[PDB]
Length: 360
Ligand SMILES: Cc1ccccc1OCC(=O)Nc1ccc2[nH]nnc2c1
Ligand SMILES: *[C@@H]1O[C@H](CO)[C@@H](O)[C@H](O)[C@H]1NC(C)=O
Image (cartoon, rainbow, N blue to C red; front, side, top):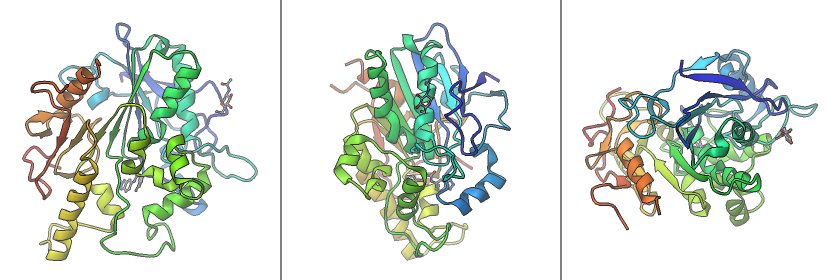
């Protein structure tokens, strides 16, 4: 009940169906910390699959049925028992209603059945919050899970630039990308992109960018250039182009990654081909995080962590995620810290080799 809905006052910034986008807010009068969380929820990339999403996932495409309040959980909780890290922060939950991995900049019109405005929704939320206390902030942490985690990578630097051009260069913009660090790897079984379920992420995102009028960070765009902006949706490719500090949270054996790799576990014995596939996926993920100084990557088969009520339970090398985020805060005061690590990547090679992995 802690977060209260506000629909955007700028009615031109809309969910997929043209209804107003919005945000849920719980203010903390004492605090100059602001947490803006980007909800996840896959994406759609053509008329037919967006139509189907509108039938059975309408809250991800429309505000018409949104409730007036939401309960803050995990990193959005205001109870220190549940949220050791930022329980006293101003809390913002931004519903994902643009189906575009937070990248879109296109309105519904005579040529567009749907609006894809994810990148504009974030900018408009930031603008409207500045009159609600964000103008006094010292840190704005843009966080997100799954498609919202990818959205952090695509938008954190644009939020920084926006605040600079609005006259607030003192607000420190940082990112926390959870479960949004995907690999454009070989699938375990492969299909040509002939419909929605057969379309590999690289091809689905390439089509999505054109359907959404998707935008990516400027430095990444200049590296990959026209026709190749889909590359900037892959964390290991976009991360090195970013200037804002970003903490990366990623399960080594993410269930969404395995799904897009056409791996479906049943509990039956894993044979050698699939064993090597899974072990190689964990090794590749670990490799992409080698030069990411702020990261938390447990060897578990799971998906998302930061808004889960029991997010405090998982540890890597004996350090929980709330502790690692606290150590990250200390490291950004402006040399490593004794017993306060920020780079926590498991080295064991199979899901649940870490005993603190979520049970399910
Ligand atoms: C794949 C990919 C590559 C680069 C960037 C984003 C991305 O995808 C975002 C997402 O949200 N994906 C997703 C997949 C499978 C899922 N199963 N359940 N939720 C799921 C979400
Ligand atoms: C409303 O949003 C649109 C799209 O982002 C933007 O072009 C316009 O300037 C905004 N209007 C105001 C008053 O902020």
